Image (tube, coloured by chain):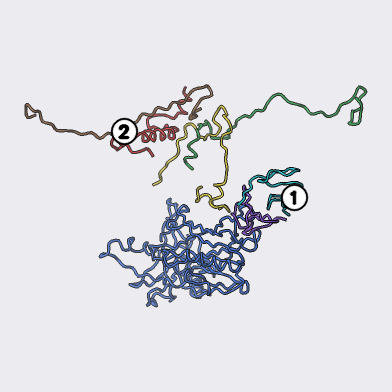
Chain colours: A red, B yellow, C green, D brown, E purple, F cyan, G blue
Amino acid sequence: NFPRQMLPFSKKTKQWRKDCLLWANQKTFFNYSLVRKSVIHKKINY
Amino acid sequence: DDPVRNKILHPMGGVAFSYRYDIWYIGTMDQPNIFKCKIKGDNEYRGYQW
Amino acid sequence: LDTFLNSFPTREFEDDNEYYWDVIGSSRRNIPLVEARDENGVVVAANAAN
Amino acid sequence: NSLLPYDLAGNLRVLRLYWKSKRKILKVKSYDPETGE
Amino acid sequence: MKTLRTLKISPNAPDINSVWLYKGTMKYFNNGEWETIG
Amino acid sequence: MKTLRTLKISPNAPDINSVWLYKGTMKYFNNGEWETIG
Amino acid sequence: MVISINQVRQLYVAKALKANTAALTTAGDIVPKADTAKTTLYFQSMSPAGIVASDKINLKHVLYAKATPSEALAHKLVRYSVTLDADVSATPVAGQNYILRLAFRQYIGLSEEDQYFKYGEVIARSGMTASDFYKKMAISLAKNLENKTESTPLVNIYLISAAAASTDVPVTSATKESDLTATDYNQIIIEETEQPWVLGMMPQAFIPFTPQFLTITVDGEDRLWGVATVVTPTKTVPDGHLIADLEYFCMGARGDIYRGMGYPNIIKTTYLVDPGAVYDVLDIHYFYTGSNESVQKSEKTITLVAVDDGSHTAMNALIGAINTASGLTIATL
């Protein structure tokens, strides 16, 4: 659950900038994009 | 202290899991001891059947 | 519980099979005695001379 | 290593996130003092 | 488990946490009563 | 009202503000004399 | 209350058996109808405003049919026998304060985190025997728990004398010491009690507890005071409030989904389950299949509900009416 981006700039506090990054290192296993190949497919090519 | 998962009560009040002592790090291992396991290129599944 | 499982790192693996890690002790050891024989080959028991 | 904090080579995992937030802005219709533009 | 620091010589009952000394008795508080030694 | 605080293990008699303890005779100072407890 | 369904659930109330479509004259009958080659079973019930039928149960497509009695659908109220621990002291210690804590766990909410605590306190004095102690702590617990002011019924507390050893004498917040006159009181039993029930708005749920004891200093080492044993129950809450709340949901499959939402304008349905009588429940769980490539199933169920007199006279006549009409070996209960 990525925190809400629809906030006034005073409500984009210091903990809110950590919540977007604690989301990032949890969903950094994710690499799916609909115009890219897999990580294991490119690793076989390299 | 979680009373929904911990169901055995202790004779001295509260759940019996509260009386469990755990020392998680004895010294510095020079590498991460406890971590979690994932697979490279394993996005978790979501699939609709409609 | 989820804040307990967030003080741990994560290692992404290449396969979904069993994974191993190798543990080591030391190299220098002491060896127990079996018996001590004197020069003619008869064992030296407790009630014996030098 | 692939999400470990350090590396056995001796390096630090640097995770740079870039993301498009949403900013509230105002469009203001102001009149020119000189001409009616 | 229960420390008693003081000993009080008096003909009256001093305190739960002290020892009551009379003529030839040494009574202390135990089990809700004054228990004598001897 | 006399409040004794220390207990002395001695073969002879200690100062009068303490309990004389020797071999099983708890002795304390009462009425001018060392009066045994037991 | 709201239950889970296996893609549908419908209930029919069986007040009597008529065995023919033309003999349906009173609201609440049931007629298990079928044809000569036993391939379709269906239940023609007389609603208060005309004859209704069921879904046509394909008899090659039934999965189970098992009818449960009313004694297996009753919630048993737990008991806790609170005695003096004979290890610490057989008689109460003449100086210590004797406290007992009752730890409730589903108070107000449903989660085991919505906890609630009540207490009982009796200071033990010199010369107080064990029967005089239980005579004091049955009053002190009932002054908290069974008071006139508490918003919910928490527990029922009784005393047991050693001569009778089975008959419970009730203690309440208004009972005085002169009513309990016995020198052989040996335990205090704390029994659960029935929370209030509102039809279709308050489900039947109970508050569980645990009598937990507070420490008393016996020989200079602080030792826990009492022991609590679960005693096999003697009082059950019957099946009346569970099947009125089960009809109320499964009438919404055949009818209106909203029951009073906006009240100048509602469609009232008349219910046939009396909430003061016990009932037996038979469930024929079936499915549907098209005779083509659409082999994916659609599970269903029906529920038939009949009044129980203890010997199951109304329901075993209904199972005897289904087995000979449709050719299932539904177990006589």
Which amino acid lies under the numbered mark 1 shown in the image of this protein? Thr
Judging depth in this view, the residue of D21 and E16 nearest the camera is: E16
Is disc 2 placed on a helix, strand or loop? loop
Judging depth in this view, the residue of D14 and B26 nearest the camera is: B26
Which amino acid lies under the numbered mark 2 shown in the image of this protein? Ser
Instruction: State whether residue G158 appears in this view.
Output: yes
Count of all numbered marks drawn on residues in the image: 2
Q: Residues within 10 Å of mark 1 (few under 14, many from 20)?
A: few
- Residue F27 at x, y = what percent? 72, 50
- Residue F14 at x, y = what percent? 70, 43
Where F9 falls versus G311 (above or below)? above
Q: In this rendering, which labeled residue sits more in front, label 1 or label 2? A: 1
- Subunit of label 1: F
Q: Residues within 10 Å of mark 2 (few under 14, many from 20)?
A: few
Q: What is the C-alpha distance between the residues marked 1 and 2?
A: 87 Å
Q: Which mark is residue F25?
A: 1
Instruction: State whether residue G246 appears in this view.
Output: no
CB within 8 Å, label 1 to label 2: no
Q: Which residue is mark 2?
A: D21
Where E3 falls versus G60 (above or below)? above
- Which residue is found at the position 54% from the left and 52% from the top? B13
- Subunit of label 2: D
- Residue G187 at x, y = what percent? 59, 66
Residue extending furthest left? D35
In the rendered structure, the answer to whether residue G198 lies left or right of residue G230 reads left
